[PDB]
């Protein structure tokens, strides 16, 4: 269905060195309600434009 | 007399139903927008809302496959072509006089003619090509004022529409026609407080069960009931 | 370790296929295929894609 196509602005995260780093940031993003999509097998996730700065800030504080 | 609120209730297509709706090209696809579980849930909620008010409700289905899937699941009586004269009169007399039976389902056999009973609420499960005028006539014949002279509206017409399907095209048309006929008319996209009721198809698996059944149907199952 | 801006598009498989067809024709639309129901698209092309999808689906002479 076309009526069900949804788009979102934001940022795609990738290039994680470890499963633990990927899941840490993925979990934090879910906790604060800004994670829109993820794929554990690729270690990627997509964060809303609104939430991106908080996720970056958390990453830089670890 | 009767003061009627007219509403279209726009219901999203479940993604699984929308997927098949697109892929299928024959009139069979009408069944996917008719049985769409969001539309069933809207119908179920409206029956609950109105039965709490002790309103009498007729639900019209022009499609027999749909008539039965809805009525039997909601445990309401239904009338269509092959319903015998005896059983039909039993149901109508129950609708009219038994306070425990205030919702019935009727197919295209209702208009016309046997004597359509009176009701305070008329819900049309489907919309199609192309009689805007038969709709208003049926609305007029059926709807009587709930005996609320103070109230703004004492009778209710709802037409349930599946979003992202050919059903919507019939809407700009119906709205224009009904208001031109002197009716108060609105579009409802979200029914206030459906999440406070226990409605069918809450799980994906139950929706998939219905989807399989619809896919098993044929183009004949998607034709309107014809009657002479 | 790396982040890139884009527009996430969530859609059914048949729509994903159609957007890929749009990209093949016009180029510079799809940045990444993410999964069976998700694409990363050029943010400046989102409205184009939505309009084109509407045309493809609504104006099909076999409707």
Image (spheres, grey):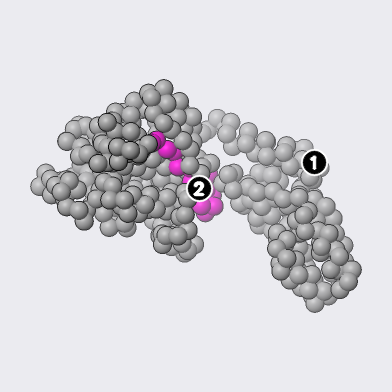
Residue B46 visible in the picture: yes
Q: What stretch is highlighted in magenta?
A: B5-28
Magenta stretch: residue B9 in it?
Answer: yes
- Percent x, y for residue A27? 74, 71
Secondary structure under the numbered disc 2 in the rendered image: loop
Residue B36 visible in the picture: no
Examine the image and state in which quarter residue B220 appears.
Answer: top left
Which mark's residue is nearer the viewer, 2 or 1?
2
- Marker disc for residue B226: none
Nearest to the observer: residue B190 or residue B220: B190
- Residue at 55% across / 30% down in the picture? C61
- Residue at 48% across / 58% down in the picture? B195
Nearest to the observer: residue B104 or residue C27: B104
- Residue at 86% across / 65% down in the picture? A57
Looking at this rendering, what residue extends furthest in the front direction? B150
Q: In which quarter of the image is the C terminus of chain A?
A: bottom right
Q: Are marks 2 and 1 on the same chain?
A: no
Looking at this rendering, what residue extends furthest in the bottom direction? A20
Label 1 marks a residue whose chain is C
What residue would you read off at disc 2?
B190
What residue would you read off at disc 1?
C44
Rate crowding at label 1 as few (under 14), some (14 to 19) or many (20 or more) other CA atoms within 10 Å: few
- Percent x, y for residue A34? 73, 61
- Percent x, y for residue B117? 20, 39
Looking at this rendering, what residue extends furthest in the top direction? B180
């Amino acid at each position: 269905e076309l009526d069900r196509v949804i788009t979102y602005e934001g940022s795609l995260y990738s290039d994680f060195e470890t499963s633990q780093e990927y899941n840490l940031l993925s979990k934090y993003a879910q906790d604060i309600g800004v994670l829109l999509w993820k794929d554990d097998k690729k270690k990627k996730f997509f964060i809303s434009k609104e939430g991106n700065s908080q996720v970056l800030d958390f990453a830089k504080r670890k | 007399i009767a003061n009627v609120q007219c509403a279209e209730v726009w219901c999203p297509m479940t993604a699984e139903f929308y997927q098949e709706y697109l892929r299928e090209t024959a009139r069979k696809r009408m069944l996917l927008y008719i049985m769409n579980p969001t539309k069933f849930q809207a119908c179920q909620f409206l029956i609950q809302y109105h039965e709490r008010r002790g309103d009498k409700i007729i639900v019209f289905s022009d499609n027999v496959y749909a008539l039965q899937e809805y009525a039997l699941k909601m445990g309401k009586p239904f009338i269509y072509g092959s319903t015998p004269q005896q059983e039909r009169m039993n149901i109508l007399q129950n609708f009219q006089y038994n306070d425990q039976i205030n919702t019935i389902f009727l197919s295209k056999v209702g208009d016309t003619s046997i004597d359509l009973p009176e009701a305070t609420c008329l819900i049309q499960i489907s919309s199609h090509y192309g009689s805007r005028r038969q709709e208003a006539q049926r609305l007029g014949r059926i709807l009587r004022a709930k005996r609320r002279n103070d109230e703004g509206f004492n009778a209710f017409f709802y037409s349930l529409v599946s979003k992202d399907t050919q059903e919507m095209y019939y809407s700009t048309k119906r709205q224009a026609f009904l208001v031109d006929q002197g009716y108060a008319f609105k579009v409802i996209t979200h029914l206030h407080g459906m999440e406070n009721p226990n409605l069918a198809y809450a799980s994906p698996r139950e929706r998939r069960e219905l989807l399989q059944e619809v896919l098993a149907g044929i183009e004949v199952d998607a034709d309107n009931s014809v009657g002479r | 370790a790396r982040a890139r801006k884009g527009a996430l598009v969530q859609c059914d498989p048949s729509i994903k296929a159609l957007i890929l067809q749009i990209d093949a024709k016009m180029s510079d639309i799809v940045l990444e295929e993410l999964d069976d129901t998700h694409l990363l698209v050029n943010p400046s092309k989102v409205e184009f894609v939505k309009h084109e999808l509407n045309r493809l689906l609504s104006k099909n002479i076999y409707n």
